[PDB]
Image (cartoon, rainbow, N blue to C red):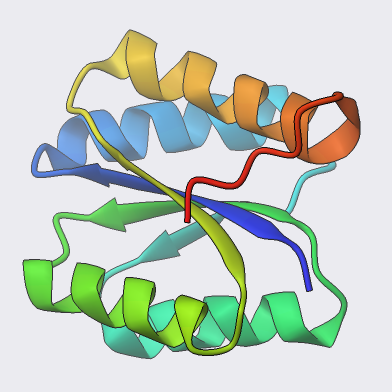
Length: 112
């Protein structure tokens, strides 16, 4: 059991860019990248194995896969946050803000 940031964008050029920046600036972090519901479920299962601060960059995944993410998480009780932004600066700072509140802050971040 843990917590995850669902980074959603239609701009895969922005997603991949920030995803690089996030993995190379934070190399000791488990970061994820989903195409469809296959990956989505593999990710929530990765949280079942122990549970780490995951950041799921969905490479322009359908609203169907977004719905699958929400459903598969909440039915199990998995804590998740959802983000819809195509701004590179937004997504970059959302990674570190997420890791900081998921690692050690006072407010237990729990969007749903």
